[PDB]
Image (tube, rainbow, N blue to C red):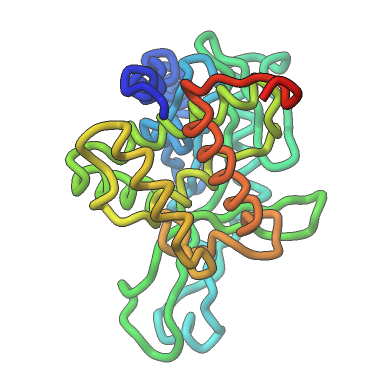
Length: 295
């Protein structure tokens, strides 16, 4: 088994002061720009937002979201029943405005386009900026105009496709689970992240448990498994996952499937591998070895 003090150290959160200032810096840059069709909101997602960061020096995941217009899954008839019209301001237009705002504030040498994000070197931490528009997922047929689930969406020019994410729901649901586990859920995520990274440092696979997939995996574990001590939590969580039917696990945002064939999803086999590595870490700790010819 792993000593409690080791698990407790692994549960520590990295500092967040510099990440928060990075967020405030991006926000201040956008405040200086004149927005032609709505001023976007700026919020954090990712590990810092969700209090699951195990370091204080990782890049900051920032969302720059336009809310004056929305993309959606409505049919033309549903749009008509709601009185909706087309926005003449596009995601492409908005992206160009955000890029100009950031370049004006930080300078061209500090702002560059990535595949899916704008990367910004601030005076605090580097920011990975997702430029997106509000996305409304509406139910079928004729329903109320307030009956929708809110996410966001962005275009990937290199892949001719739209991505829809739900970071606000990811945050909301993780916070709710943390409240209901007497604040053990987020320390437990960090414990497993640090356990994973400890193994990767020793040669375990780089993709043993990508952070987002690991959070989603743990989100599916009953609240009763989190608490008491870190040793009891480590074993109760891993033993429940080993016996669980993973196939219907949902992401923490409540919208997506965790497992599937797309690269946006994990695989059950990768999750089972993570469980095997946690088992081995636990059972191997404190054990003596020798070569088989000395047994």
